[PDB]
Length: 51
Length: 51
Image 1 (tube, rainbow over the protein chains, first blue to last red):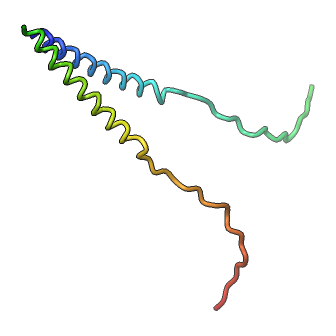
Image 2 (tube, chains in turn blue, red):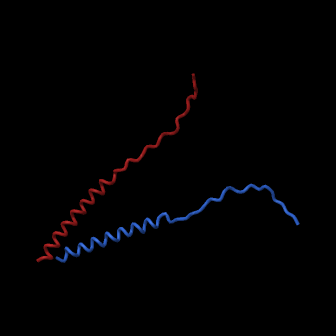
Image 3 (cartoon, rainbow over the protein chains, first blue to last red):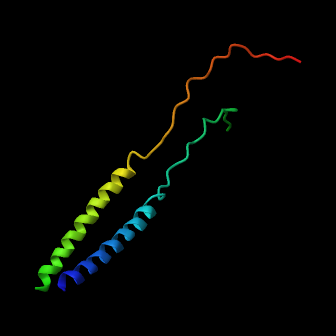
């Protein structure tokens, strides 16, 4: 009755690993920060200097 | 003679499930509708109004 018991334990193992892959994949996603785009250059109201 | 009979029934089972996977996969495909792309904007022949 060896084959019958062997097959059962193998089925359970592969199911458990697949579900674990899902959690890891989805957690991996939506895990990217990125950047902001600086606005257009600031208009120059004045440039001057003093002592 | 247990192992000999056990193995045979297990072989048949896995073959049947694989063929069933195929039908389901292929049926799943080619099952996407999609969309049409509206033509370019309609040229305006006239805009008017009355009482």
